[PDB]
Each structure stands twice: as C-alpha cells, then as structure tokens.
Image (cartoon, rainbow, N blue to C red; front, side, top):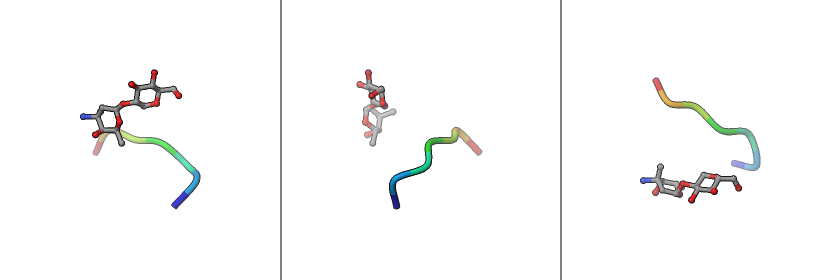
Length: 7
Ligand SMILES: *[C@@H]1O[C@H](CO)[C@@H](O)[C@H](O)[C@H]1O[C@H]1C[C@](C)(N)[C@H](O)[C@H](C)O1
C-alpha cells in the first residue's frame, strides 16, 4: 500500500 483511496 502507501497510496490512498477510497474505492
Ligand atoms: C487515511 O490517511 C489519512 C492521511 O494520512 C489519515 O488522516 C486517515 O486517518 C487515514 O484513514 C484511516 C481510516 C480508514 C479510511 N478507515 C482506513 O482504515 C485508512 C487505512 O486509515
């Protein structure tokens, strides 16, 4: 991970 979202 390390990214974000939310999906
Ligand atoms: C997502 O990242 C932001 C920026 O660093 C934080 O401020 C936030 O608390 C964080 O969201 C938490 C809560 C969430 C959305 N339910 C997920 O569990 C994420 C991984 O962590």
